[PDB]
Image: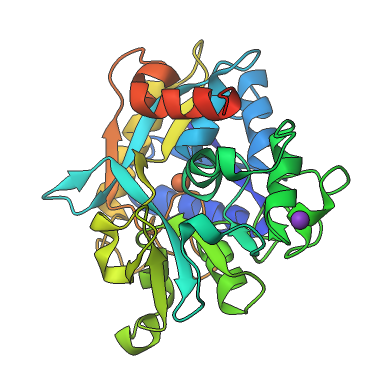
Length: 329
Ligand SMILES: [Fe+3]
Ligand SMILES: [K+]
């Protein structure tokens, strides 16, 4: 069934990808689907490679999946991740704003604070939180990047150009767009909050649970709700900024090997899915969190035939992005 050149971003993913290829080869029959690893510096390069036919697949955050659709790459979502459980799969998750208990400020008081973002253009770490604070931001608001750097008093927005918007890398100099940046991603934005570099971390509802196994430690943290109040991390369903589409694997539209990508992932979630193997795991890793696929994922679901990004993502979230990228006050 040929090979799916998987795009790994940086060395940790590269390692897990190499492990993914070995283990798959050790079980799936010589005729089945195999995996190859193409290592890139950022998801941006991953998107260029796939569109150039030097790679075939990569998993992306909804917001990045939207971007991958715009020309001249026009990549399509082919396999989505689902969370929660296999019995009740959820193809969405909750963006939340985590903070340290007794920090003393609600949502309408973020101005002047320090922000820890998962990454620029990501749903929970950027599109959702910045969309909601769009008008609180100082004018001019365009370019957005600079208005955000001005609203807060120091941030970490991975993938942002540190040369044009220095304050966006104040909490993580260089704004590295990969695990090389320790404050990159969910658990990265959380560590930025925990080490005390920032005051708030825009991540997902499961992030803190992936980092603090003891409730005692977690009680020293809270969520900022939309009604300008705070609630425990356990109460995200009623204290989140928004609900968003699940991360999804994207591929080319022509000669995209979507059937093979899915066949590879479906067989892979049976062999190495949640609690399935003692040799290898798809949704966890000894080299780091959320490498290739997010840790909170429980499996995969095949995206309907020929579906494009707009359709998959859905109108509500597409609008949310269009509004943030346009919108007025
Ligand atoms: Fe995300
Ligand atoms: K500022």
